[PDB]
Image (cartoon, rainbow, N blue to C red):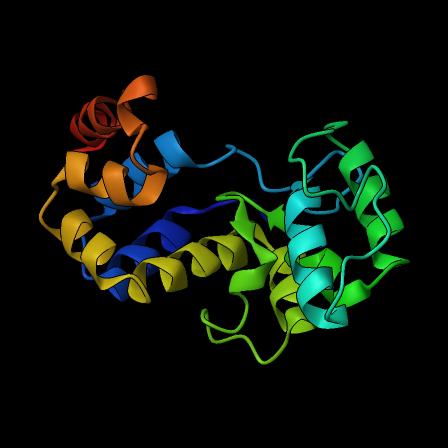
Length: 187
């Protein structure tokens, strides 16, 4: 499958108005490294508590509870088996299921499709299948629609970036220091 090129990094850097070293640093620290499984489908993690929340909102009442639709988070099988979980959830409701997986290099939740400017959940999904460059573009859009994160990236304020991107427990995995060290390694 089409993996990340120097041009993918340069295009992303240009679109975000940051240096290439910043994009490589955030990719090294925040990505899954590869955006695709051996089978050629995008890497996903299926989030059954998002499936429960989104299908509840759609139906106006609680859906059936099972291993892929449950207010209790977890129950991961990992790797290719997450596609089997997605398939079971699609057979409950396709749009809720696709929105309840995290996709590609940066593990972006499908429920962000509309905010990210995709025409539909399906267009978001097609962008995950297209290439690693397309998945990096999903990440670019995510930064653009989050100006405070965008500004932290531009200013190389790794702690502010990690607090907003990784959340309040970012320091548990030292995300700020990993970003700073990665940046120095590429600069």
